[PDB]
Length: 297
View (cartoon, helix red, strand yellow):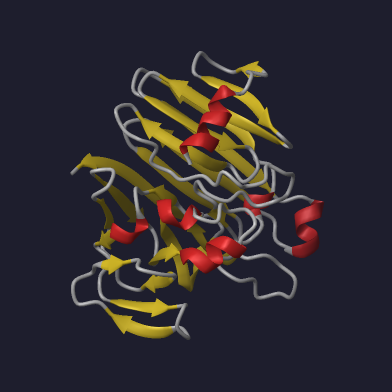
């Protein structure tokens, strides 16, 4: 991850937005790069996709694939994919997993900054193109706060019912020692025939391919990382579910936008609204949010 992320911060500035915010470009994609005294972070306009976040004094918090394409319309591997207006495999033949918002260019609508960090608002709207495959008008906003902590808030305006996720990839020293706590009790194991399991202590380990939807997780998931000597707190709001995922080695090998050994240095802990649909009116827009906090261990 650190190598690919260092590539982004080495890129020429195409436009200086503010003293800490610049636009740059990698292959096809326009990037917004935050290089602030208290935090480094970067985004693609495509998918309003948070690619990296490193608060001062900490190692990179988000994992980004050193093998991901940066191509128009192609989902980025790593960071925090915004999965909207569906989570997981498409109901319709030929549609991708995790919706279509992560594939389209969002506008950077607003931002502000101070000595502590930066706030940014990205917007996606329906168009004749989106209405071709999803006949609902919408305006989707992704608001970020990047600083000592990282806040992500997704808000969908329209009249529709959806499922969604903030599909975060967290940089870990070694997946073989990672455990995640605060995951509650019941879960659906997608690796094993969607069987429902029950944890008695809310603690998940990732010895191999793991793909679980937690039905009753606590507000705060805690990723314990003995190798980087830290915990990452992932706080979920307005959600129904948390997903824990690591593809393990076979899948890591066959995924072309992943390094063969990529699975070693991330775990996904996702804020999810999947087991029932979320209402947007009308106007009470839907919301889904995740806050990330790093602590020593």
